Each structure stands twice: as structure tokens, then as C-alpha cells.
Amino acid sequence: DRQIKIWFQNRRMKWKK
Image (tube, rainbow, N blue to C red; front, top):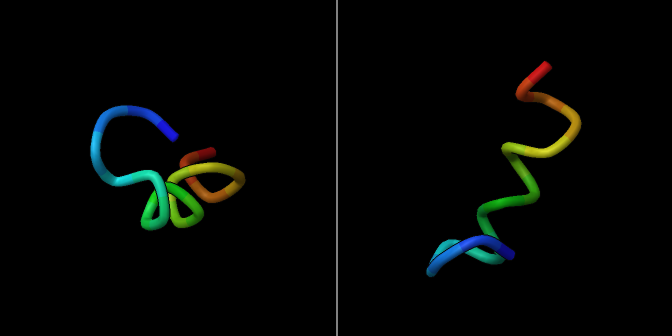
């Protein structure tokens, strides 16, 4: 959870690497 995209955040977690 960051701002509004708390669910989609699952895409920018261990993949942002």
C-alpha cells in the first residue's frame, strides 16, 4: 500500500527490481 494503488502494488514489489 502506497497511495491509492494498494492492490496493484503487488506488481511493483518484487518485480520492480
